[PDB]
Length: 146
Length: 146
Ligand SMILES: COCCN/C=C1/C(=O)N(C)c2ccc(C(F)(F)F)cc2N(c2ccccc2)C1=O
Ligand SMILES: COCCN/C=C1/C(=O)N(C)c2ccc(C(F)(F)F)cc2N(c2ccccc2)C1=O
Ligand code: NA
Ligand code: NA
Image (cartoon, rainbow over all chains, first blue to last red; front, side, top):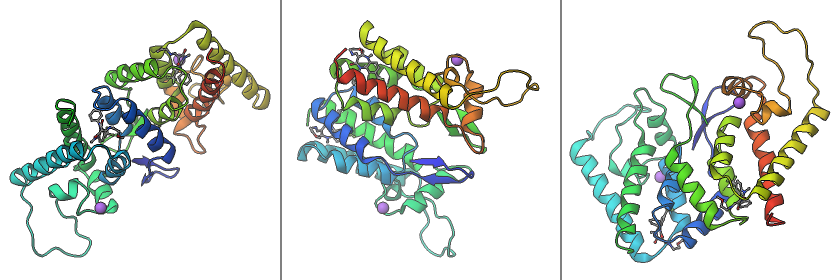
């Protein structure tokens, strides 16, 4: 997630491995449990898409449940593009481009571009947007158990 | 916890009731379980003493376990005073005073004074210090189950 250092700068701070390890243990004990969702949202506060994917990849899960999660994310990303089309073409070096669904999901964006959108004014909270997509998918999983 | 708003300012953001509710459910299911500790540290990122006490009070627990926790905190606070004595007496209005153990524990300090120490340069991370005392006590509890 993003936090301000001892100067003023908004810097990225990776998620602690000990937090990740404890989290996977929680999910393992409360598989498909609704209470895990508010906890997921709590631990991902200020998280960038990169951080979110690290959490998702670390947890893993059932092949099938991961599918519904990915499909949900993909569906929401395509819905973002349908509503927020981005222009392709000429852009000067260092110019900020508008994020597409795949950028919000961290697939086609770097940590630096994610931080840029998140610390911009007006900000494009790509971390918050992606988290919502994930939570939608998690809420879908709990309701099928697959 | 403290977070920067849409201007630049370091503002306080209370813990979500939904997070608190989910957390108490976790502790209830994993009573005295070591894995809860890394999770406690994760959710209290950037937390002020006020936030920490809200979490502690919300969780509650066994009369006896709460005792060892309080006694541990009290013991560490007295140890902080023994090593970092603070001068009493004349101080101008609005002057920043050095925190004593009771201030770090949020007993004799306001949310505003806690934020002041935490956003000062060099900072007095009262939230981090208090969190360590709590985690020491939690590690004590797990090892007695009381
Ligand atoms: C470590 O795996 C052990 C067995 N549990 C697997 C699960 C699963 O298959 N998926 C795909 C995932 C993926 C990410 C997460 C996340 F960390 F993000 F929360 C939870 C989660 N949930 C889940 C979903 C909804 C509500 C509660 C838990 C599971 O139970
Ligand atoms: C809601 O209560 C249901 C039964 N569990 C009670 C417990 C207890 O009596 N105390 C005093 C506390 C107090 C705060 C916390 C905190 F939220 F901060 F983690 C955990 C905790 N732990 C605890 C201690 C060490 C490791 C894991 C859990 C307990 O089990
Ligand atoms: Na990437
Ligand atoms: Na207070």
